[PDB]
Length: 96
Ligand SMILES: [Cu+2]
Image 1 (cartoon, rainbow, N blue to C red):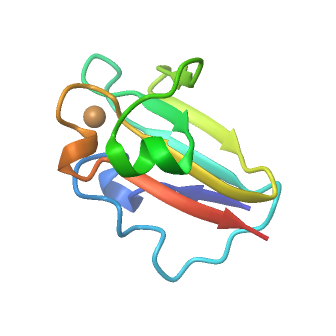
Image 2 (cartoon, rainbow, N blue to C red; image 1 turned 180 degrees about the vertical axis):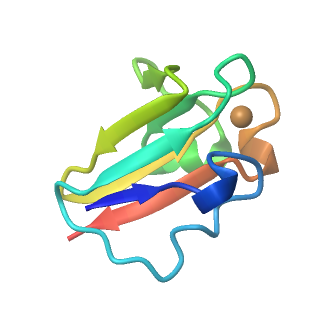
C-alpha cells in the first residue's frame, strides 16, 4: 500500500505526528511531496532522528515526489535543511 506523507499538506513542518495510528507493513511505500528547492528527504538512524544530526552516508532524496519502499522494521526520515528537523520535519515508522 501507498501512503502520502502529511496527506494533502505533503512533506512539511511539524509533521512528526502523521504516523500516529497507522499500521505499516514491509513493502509499503511512503510518498513524499514537496518543493526540492526548500526541502529534502534523508534516511537516518534512530540517533540521527533524535538529535537531528545526519549520519555519514545517509541517503538523500530530492525529486519532489519520492516513493520510498519500507523495509521490515524501523525507518527514520528527516528534512536536513537548516532548522527543519528541529521544527518537526521528521517521521519515525515501524513496518511489520
Ligand atoms: Cu524541510
